[PDB]
Each structure stands twice: as structure tokens, then as C-alpha cells.
Length: 88
Image 1 (cartoon, helix red, strand yellow):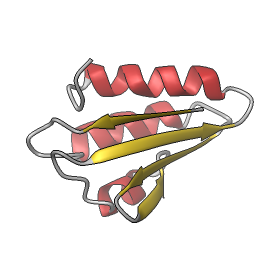
Image 2 (cartoon, rainbow, N blue to C red):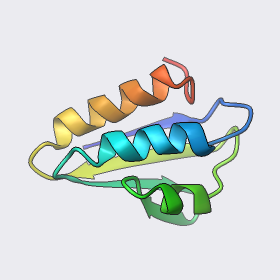
Image 3 (tube, one colour):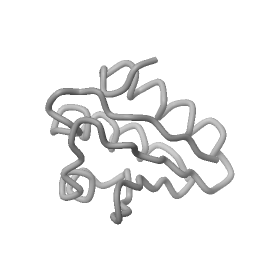
Image 4 (cartoon, rainbow, N blue to C red):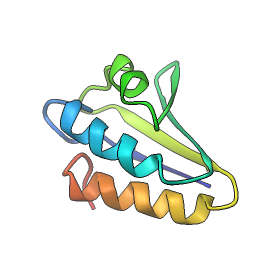
């Protein structure tokens, strides 16, 4: 399962949103990867996500693989919207 979106947050994918996303992703059995530029990371890891240093305008792709992938993708998309990282 997957979705792509453009990061519209003016600070990028920074601590607050990364922390919230890592928490949310960690609930899922699925493997949840975040892809940006040439980098791929585990969305469940705040360090991994911060290390990606995703900045505004970057188009990211979230890929969920696993038994709860469909829920996971929606949960993650909503989370991004809720944290204002992306536009709903």
C-alpha cells in the first residue's frame, strides 16, 4: 500500500511530526517505509526519519507492506494531514 505527497511544512519533516509519525507507524505490524530523493527510511524510527532531513517541497512516498497495510497507510496519511505536514 502506498501514497505520495508533497511536504508543505515550512520547516520540513521535523521533530514534532517525525515523533508523531514514528509513534503512529509503530502501532502497525506492516513494514512502513518513507522514501525521499535517493533515501529510504523506516517510518517507525524517529532517528531514521530525522536523518533523512526531508525539507519543504520534497515529494515523499510512504509504502506499507503487511497485513494491516491498508489501515496503516490511511492512519499515516491522516497523521500527516493532522500535523499539517502535508495538505489534505
